[PDB]
Amino acid sequence: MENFPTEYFLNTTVRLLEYIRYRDSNYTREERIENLHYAYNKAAHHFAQPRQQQLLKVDPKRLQASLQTIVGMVVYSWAKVSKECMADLSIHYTYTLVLDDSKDDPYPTMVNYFDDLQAGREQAHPWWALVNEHFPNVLRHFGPFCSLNLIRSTLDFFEGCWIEQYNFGGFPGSHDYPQFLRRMNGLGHCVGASLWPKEQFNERSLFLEITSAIAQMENWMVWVNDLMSFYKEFDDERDQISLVKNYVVSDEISLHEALEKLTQDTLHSSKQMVAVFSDKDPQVMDTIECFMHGYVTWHLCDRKYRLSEIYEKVKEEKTEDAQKFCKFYEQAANVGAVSPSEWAYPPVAQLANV
Ligand SMILES: [Mg+2]
């Protein structure tokens, strides 16, 4: 397919939004902006500190771009958590996003990882040094079980990045590779457990639902992301590996077949998500429904995924899908589309220079 599956894409997206029950929220734009700025402001000051500035080797521009995409992701999806929680999660997920930027071999700095860890010595790898120092600010919002999940997933993520450094799409015939890697760097368990602050949820009382939420949320979150990202990544000769591209290489199937597989998982995942949590604790179903919706809004509104382009193409096309799509889009935009100038300021560099 030298061309983007525009039709096919539009279809599944609508089906997906329908399945999850994509609709309006009592989360106003004035509320969204309130939070966006709160989160961004705390994070910005954090990354602007000299220590963070030294140890984190990231280009100023990308750091700004990353922080902004992450604050957005967090505020729009963790709708029911506190302002401080959105902020702290924003800092954590910004660190993770930034690590996918390093080309640097982890190996030499990981040689004494466990011995330093057990001894309480600052880690050799600067990233760990920063993240582990910051971690308590995130972990304070959760109980021990949810905390353990955040810790593991982040550790899993670190290995994932390491593996990704080899741009390996898996050996042909290695069917278990693709999902193995995707889970490794999807932060699924991190996301899943960070949805339940101990301030508004009892980890022990809701242990079974939380666990189930983590288990199911992990795959939904990553597959929805892989799907929504399929468009930007299509003509990106720079991005060589991805769940879909890897299915292709490892499963030895066509890109169509691979994209096919993703869609079946995504939709089935959606259907089962609702099936399971509808009749459960209302507060749980609420956090979950909001995350799914917010997560979708975010993808549709953040420039990174460039979905606006797909809009301004089928904008006046008159097929069923086409319209149901554009309708959903505009819905998002209403509370989603927000000029950065309304919340993301001043730039991190400016704060860093002061
Ligand atoms: Mg990729």
Image (cartoon, rainbow, N blue to C red):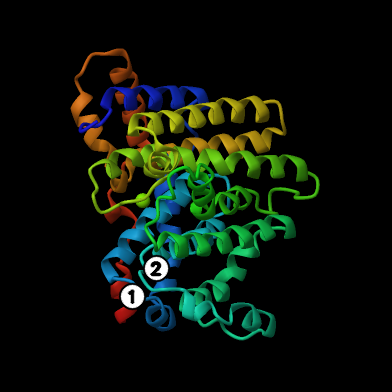
Relative to residue 13, is residue 70 depicted above or below? below
Residue 77 in view (yes/no):
yes
Query: What distance separates the C-alpha of mark 2 from that of mark 1?
Result: 8 Å
Q: Secondary structure at mark 2?
A: helix
Q: Amino acid at mark 1?
A: Leu
Q: Secondary structure at mark 1?
A: helix
Horizontal and vertical percent position of residue 266: 49, 32
Which is more toward the observer, 108 or 151? 108
Which is more toward the observer, 151 or 290? 151
Horizontal and vertical percent position of residue 163: 46, 61
Q: Which residue is mark 2?
A: 44
Residue that appears at 64% across and 78% down: 114
Contact (Cβ within 8 Å) of mark 2 with mark 1 = yes
Horizontal and vertical percent position of residue 162: 46, 65
Q: Which residue is mark 1?
A: 351
Residue that appears at 59% across and 78% down: 113
Q: Residues within 10 Å of mark 1 (few under 14, many from 20)?
A: some
Give the side of residue 50 with respect to residue 200, left or right: left
Residue 87 in view (yes/no):
no
Horizontal and vertical percent position of residue 205: 80, 45
Q: Quadrant of the C terminus?
A: bottom left
The answer to whether the beta carbon of the residue marked 2 is less than 8 Å from any atom of ligand 1 is no
